Image (cartoon, rainbow over all chains, first blue to last red; front, side, top):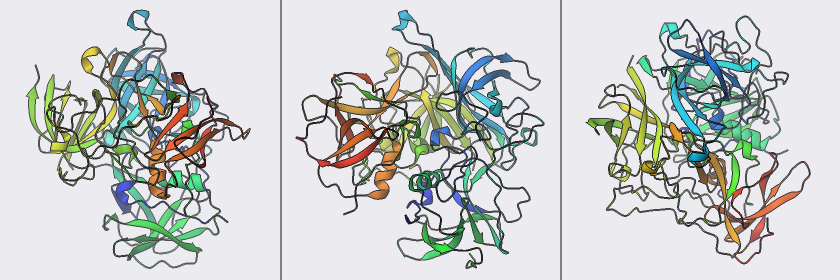
Length: 315
Length: 305
């Protein structure tokens, strides 16, 4: 049995699996009322990707496809429909057992980024090179027009005309447009991947602590804003590098729970211990919300396989 | 002796180490006249990061700092002090060419500047950093970016540059992926550089991992070629396997058929050569990936492609 391992990476060497951001802090929120069921950054300890999770850091909250036409929408701005493919350019097959194309955003909000286009057709007078354009854009994932499982989404621009129909189009995510009440940011609310009033399918399962006194432990990143007030964050269950490592190793899981220790390598001391669950998430024994204030040189080390009955030393 | 290994990843599972892009194709260009001495995506086979290379995919061509002054070019420019990406002050006496993650090529890099004030107020705008400009002096702790926005950028507030593509590849935009910026300005020599790379055996050429980079406007199909993908940098850093010679033999394999499509030399300093006498993409099945075979030497003759 190939021994289970985690990469050796400090917080300052990790990135978020739910948005292209560095990990800023470890975080807990025990009184969270929402069901935690994110779809990016989902991977079992034996290397099975789940939900909409894919391996590329460039693929998280990205889209690839083609603009069809400008469309009318009651909301502010200029709106555009785009078909979407798989990130690798192949047609998205809705019959595959996934919730949406891999990399699709997994939360409600106004995602801000850049739409760019490189034309298929080239100009002989320009050395047989294609024309290009890029503009800021917003994708409202709670919109009834957000239907990535059906191979179509909509985005809005401040630019009023310089977006071309029928041309290859890329969305590069950057942050959120707003976190005002009217922008419906909720990191634990899933989009409706096939539109208003349909049930999502093929989801990665919800995660929760089951042992009294335990809460989920998250890898938290602060996400940029185009405007307005706020300090919004995106919390992932495991960083993207862990997804990548587990996928590579695919080590057999010898129980449902791996005991891990958060260590300071200089001192050699254990700062705290955590349970790393088979389905790919952490719990700790902690009774407060907020950041974990820990030495910058810290990282998780696999200790041993334990079981559900194991009692964690309080943080 | 910890055995050397490469990750098991198809091209479709790899990202560029010189710009935040997926790898699109493997690529050669034997008649390249420029010295190849990129500074991102540089790592020895035994796990030593070099140049401006760091581990985060989000750190490649990124900056962090604070804006200090608005200056109208006659679009709007903004002077920016830069720190290390982790927020600590950049120490110019450290043995690096510039803050880790600093872009390693000449051009107009297009992206988004965002700010969160010290609930806080926020703003973000499209921005361009001309890395060939006299004002591009990251080794001295300062750079300049330009915006189409004329006023709504704040001074003395935390600022992030998220790279997206290039502004232009027109003649006057000075895009050249193999020309290094002058990290301290035009009259000063760059220092602490990762070494240049080249084939040393007749009939060999460099093999690159190529990504196409977006453009804000204009005509073009620009690309950025890296020596190894970011995942290889990350893997080598993790493993730190001792290098048993100066050259590793690797094979590009189709795992379904088990057949080797071609072989390449993976050199100690962290780059590939192949025996190919043509320029352009390598046409290979999407399931293919490189596997370590054995340690060889400079005199080893690669099977021609």
